[PDB]
Amino acid sequence: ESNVLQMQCKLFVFDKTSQSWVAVGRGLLRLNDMASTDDGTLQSRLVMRTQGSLRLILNTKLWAQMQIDKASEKSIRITAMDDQGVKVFLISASSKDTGQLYAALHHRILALRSRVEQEQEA
């Protein structure tokens, strides 16, 4: 793996019961790339650990069907796969980090989508 970016941020999960964001808390978020040594094909993931205690609170692989929306100047709404699992989460950060994260995710997802439509959608 190669680290693409690292940023301080705050993570929220969407709670279907209360129909509201539930704050998980702050941590260091990394976007990591891993290129296949056979196809050069790219897989990427978002990994986040709490500050201080370094406990894992996010480890989500990027997929073509993942949707990313800039929910505000300082936040990004993301979907994920995989029950009782949380489907939607929110990353809040500085305006600058949010912009960088959005751009990085956008291009990776766009690449994945291009690949899927060529491979699986004729």
Image (spheres, grey):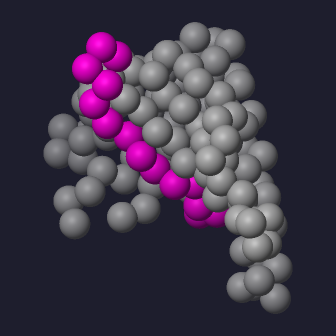
The residue lying at 79 percent from left, 72 percent from top is 39
Residue 104's quadrant in the figure? top right
Q: Over which residues does the magenta segment extend? A: 51-65
Q: Residue furthest front?
A: 37
Q: Nearer the viewer, residue 109 or 2?
A: 2
Q: Is residue 26 above or below residue 107?
A: above
In the image, residue 111 lies at what x, y percent?
79, 58
Quadrant into which the C terminus falls: bottom right
In the image, residue 3 lies at what x, y percent?
64, 35
Q: Nearer the viewer, residue 72 or 122?
A: 122
The residue lying at 37 percent from left, 29 percent from top is 49
* 8 displayed left or right of 110: left
* 64 displayed left or right of 11: right
Q: How many marks?
A: 0
Q: Is residue 90 above or below residue 37?
A: above
Q: Nearer the viewer, residue 57 or 109?
A: 57
| One can see residue 113 in this view | no
In the image, residue 115 lies at what x, y percent?
78, 71
The residue lying at 43 percent from left, 62 percent from top is 81
